[PDB]
Amino acid sequence: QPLEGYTLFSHRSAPNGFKVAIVLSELGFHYNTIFLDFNLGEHRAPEFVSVNPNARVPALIDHGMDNLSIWESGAILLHLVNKYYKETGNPLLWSDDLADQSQINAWLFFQTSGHAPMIGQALHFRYFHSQKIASAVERYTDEVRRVYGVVEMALAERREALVMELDTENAAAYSAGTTPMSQSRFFDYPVWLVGDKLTIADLAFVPWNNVVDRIGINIKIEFPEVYKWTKHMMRRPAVIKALRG
Amino acid sequence: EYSRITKFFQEQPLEGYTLFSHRSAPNGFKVAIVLSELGFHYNTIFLDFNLGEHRAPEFVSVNPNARVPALIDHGMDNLSIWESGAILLHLVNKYYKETGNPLLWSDDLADQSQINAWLFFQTSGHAPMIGQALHFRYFHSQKIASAVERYTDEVRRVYGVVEMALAERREALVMELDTENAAAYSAGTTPMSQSRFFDYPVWLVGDKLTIADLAFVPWNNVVDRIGINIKIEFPEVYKWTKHMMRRPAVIKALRGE
């Protein structure tokens, strides 16, 4: 076990595994990746249960801090941004403002408990359950859509503000609905969930967005803002260099 | 309708806290609990989704998910925090920042990470599973035994991870204190289950009560509705919850306030 660096226990499919890799990369941390293979029982295998009681990906070992283990992608990101800010004095992907950090946590916990889990069941009942049961598939498909509605309405709100301050010349127009914000030349430019800066709250959704297509959800069509917002993230070098393996 | 909710936002205080909850809401009691343990004075407003109080304009903007619990930290320009996981963390950052003492938290980066590990575990794998078992076992448009069975299996699996974890904390506690019997306990001569400190409280993180432990209290008192008999199959969890459920602040939180 190395005494400097990080080790990330993941799995080829694991979306929360790519989520950690992403943040790990955006922050310039050097990490090793070990893909546990559950089709042999290495996830519940004791050497790892010590690192993660939940016996599953994703898990992180902070070699710097006496090989400390952090399971649960949500906690891993808060540990990573905290350590990064403590080290440089620069809150990259985070915020040195308590009010912003709570809003960031709000969206982070909202993603980990109300997005990934709903997408998870939506998949189960649609692909792995022991029988086709529509009422159950539609339950998560509907819930997952509602959550994208929440995210989408928030981003359109942040956008409205931007497109309405860098173009106060036609604000009332882009506000009354008379004319779509699609026509403002200040559209394209990226907006985020909190702090008008990229943070882990925005990143936490990406690995899960690339997959709600196999659940029948077409973000491109039914969630415009969520679409741009994802496209802005996928286009990041660090993310590109991360997503895959 | 929701004029009351729109009224409240026209008379917010400049200090104190307001907690939007619901009689059933377990994460509502979870915030009340931590709010109480930290000595914070709060007002509680039970939204009745029946009159669409959650659809009120003022509520949704201060809380995008339009669900409960939601905490307004009036002292901080009515800063609104809508996730239960985010309400706990905020509360502890403030208490530590103010008093300079990490009650229910920690001032060591390593410990905080362990705390947040469990915190995310409960809010993301524990509460949501229990919710699905409750749904298929009681409110879903048709009975799907396969569904009910799976979600009751998962809470039991999750409860197993917290059990084996507290079981480790106990083995470590009974071996540290009660040194007049450590040799045996390890040798195998004595069961160790008969140590004087066997019913003593063990905590998930740092040998102290944290928000990682309390988060489970509300959900622990609910799993009896899906068959889980904690006292039997999850003894360690049993003592742990009992210890917590016996604290004056927690019982104050419980019996509504």
Image: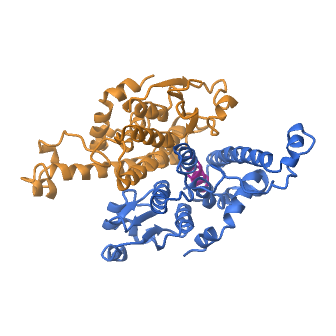
Chain colours: A orange, B blue
Query: What number of labels is visible?
Result: 0
Residue A85 location, x and y as percent?
Answer: 39, 41
| Quadrant that contains the N terminus of chain B | bottom left
Q: Determine whether A2 is above or below B231 in the image.
A: above
View extreme (right): residue: B189
Question: What span is in magenta?
Answer: B124-135
| Quadrant that contains the C terminus of chain B | bottom right
Residue B169 in view? yes
The front one of A110 and B180 is B180
Q: Residue A165 vs residue A49: left or right?
A: left
Residue B155 location, x and y as percent?
Answer: 65, 48
Residue B33 location, x and y as percent?
Answer: 57, 65
Q: Is residue A24 magenta?
A: no
Q: Main secondary structure of the magenta part?
A: helix
Q: Determine whether A74 is above or below A34 in the image.
A: below
Please tell me which residue is depicted at 91% across the width and 45% down the height of the picture. B190
Please tell me which residue is depicted at 53% across the width and 60% down the height of the picture. B27
Residue A216 in view? no
Q: Quadrant of residue A82?
A: top left
Residue B202 location, x and y as percent?
Answer: 71, 53
Please tell me which residue is depicted at 50% across the width and 31% down the height of the picture. A14
Q: Determine whether B231 is above or below B32 in the image.
A: above
Q: Determine whether B26 is above or below A119 in the image.
A: below
Q: Residue A50 vs residue A109: left or right?
A: right
Q: Quadrant of residue A71?
A: top right
